[PDB]
Length: 106
Length: 106
Ligand SMILES: [Cl-]
Ligand SMILES: [Cl-]
Ligand SMILES: [Cl-]
Ligand SMILES: [Cl-]
Ligand SMILES: [Cl-]
Ligand SMILES: [Cl-]
Ligand SMILES: [Cl-]
Ligand SMILES: [Cl-]
Ligand SMILES: [Cl-]
Ligand SMILES: [Cl-]
Ligand SMILES: [Cl-]
Ligand SMILES: [Cl-]
Ligand code: NA
Ligand code: NA
Ligand code: NA
Ligand code: NA
Ligand code: NA
Ligand code: NA
Image (cartoon, rainbow over all chains, first blue to last red; front, side, top):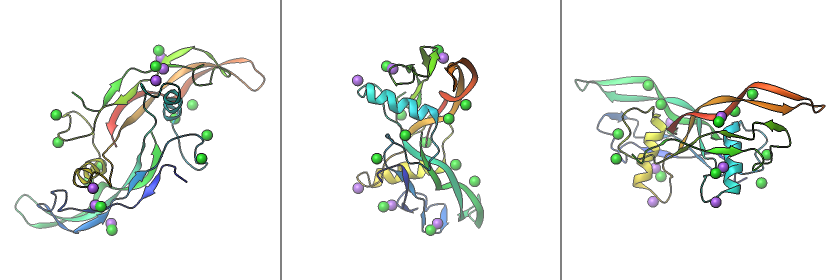
């Protein structure tokens, strides 16, 4: 519906220069938040008042003030197999903030 | 330093069609978050891992994946004088989420 939402983003750790310390997995589903912040809103979302006020000021003064932005509002962990100070392969069971759980306009 | 930060944004309630129910004040300091999300980061900020990973994927695939976005990460209340169901002028002492307290890349 052209509104702020979660969509797929497969991240390869080698592509981002993290494969020097992340051994596994090779790739993971990080998701991303894409779409607009405009009126009217999706009826099942959690908007802030600052995002609604800024979006309205944007409409009136579009060259000076930016619209609201679609961003992750909650993140989930993943497990990684990483190399510790000596190099030993070690499991990090809950590696926080790697994957989008919820999107919203902020 | 061209990095994500708090900057002034004076909001007039009439400009955004809220003066029908907000009587006072006329205008308030809402702030906004402006600036880039790029490497290297400001050394005193609170970045998420998803924002760092997405920014790096953006660098590699700039046409497909967007960069991180500079947004409010904490909001503060203001007091408003508002009209209640009958029209009586009523103070809302803590009207949440009207003003930026902190900015960050998300
Ligand atoms: Cl991709
Ligand atoms: Cl996965
Ligand atoms: Cl709406
Ligand atoms: Cl629509
Ligand atoms: Cl809010
Ligand atoms: Cl962690
Ligand atoms: Cl203005
Ligand atoms: Cl003020
Ligand atoms: Cl950095
Ligand atoms: Cl710099
Ligand atoms: Cl994080
Ligand atoms: Cl409130
Ligand atoms: Na990718
Ligand atoms: Na995954
Ligand atoms: Na303008
Ligand atoms: Na304004
Ligand atoms: Na104020
Ligand atoms: Na590309």
